[PDB]
Amino acid sequence: TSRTHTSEVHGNAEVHASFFDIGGSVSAGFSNSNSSTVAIDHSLSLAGE
Amino acid sequence: NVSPEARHPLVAAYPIVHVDMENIILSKNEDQSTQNTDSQTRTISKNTS
Image 1 (cartoon, rainbow over the protein chains, first blue to last red):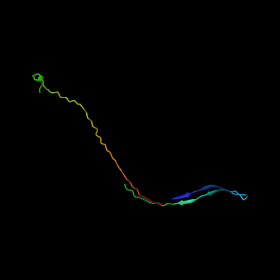
Image 2: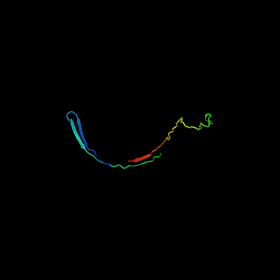
Image 3: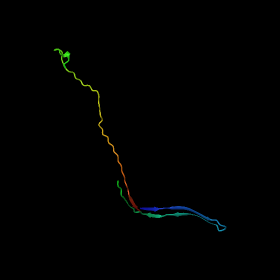
Image 4: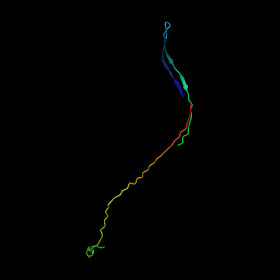
């Protein structure tokens, strides 16, 4: 069983250089993910010495 | 075999026996052992997830 919290911090930046309609966008980010991961395993082995 | 000096009635005849040791052979009572062992193991497995 695993329940994972993945917090995120982030910084972002863009720009678009043109003649007169030049556009820019610097930014950031914040995010989380509540990921509950289960895994069911069934295995075997046949050893002979 | 009675020596000729002791064949007079006044001289006694008698043996003088003594034992002298010439060697001593001691032998350590102790028991060794050795062993050699080969092996071959084949493992065949399976796993689901």
